[PDB]
Image (cartoon, rainbow, N blue to C red; front, side, top):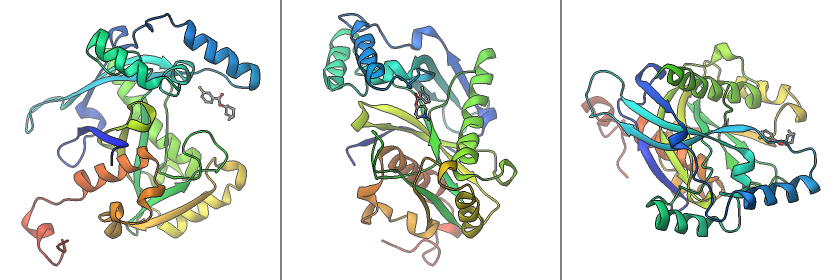
Length: 291
Ligand SMILES: CN1CCC(OC(=O)c2cccc(F)c2)CC1
């Protein structure tokens, strides 16, 4: 799967909010482009003169994520974050020249990402009471990954001392994206666990935090809530469900070629961190069938 690489696999079946520290610092920002940020401004002007209803928004930038020694006490993960924007994304990661920017960042900074916006996404492996995961179909008309399968998620917007507020906004935002797109009540959702971080190589290496969330509704009840919003209550064009039993071998199915890279990231991390049991009971052949 060349279009997704794992930056982080969390221990303990995934990390809760209270085990994660953030460092939000301008040291973690994108570096100015070699020929100046005027190249970003030019791409943005061209875009607004065609679609003048577009607006900019701030975004979190992922610099790096350091895990503690396994089995340790205290905070288990440090997220190093800076700030970026939708405008900086369109002029860097989404640019036709994005590979040239990666090569120049290797040359100048020893860092393929130094000249990239790299906005942090969030996605969820969302499980129902009857043991299915939730999938959404993307419109065939949008710019990014048209007609492909996604999971719930989005790109959160700003507003360890300022750190703990940032970690809270990341966890909050994955629940808000589920309520906004799937139309589920907030009280049917568990607190999220962070499973890991995946990178989208088709989008010059921009990263998404992938989370596990449990819902107290069945697949039939989740479907009713999604549909009862009507066509204007969601950006996706349809909802569907795959048994957690069958998610184990999804990379061997025809579905795999229709999944966008960030959804492939969510499913690989679900399989390694929530699946793949370590104990004698769940690891027994009748419960973990070979092959
Ligand atoms: C929904 N509608 C209006 C907004 C358009 O998108 C944006 O201009 C945009 C939306 C969110 C964040 C952002 F930075 C930019 C898409 C069509």
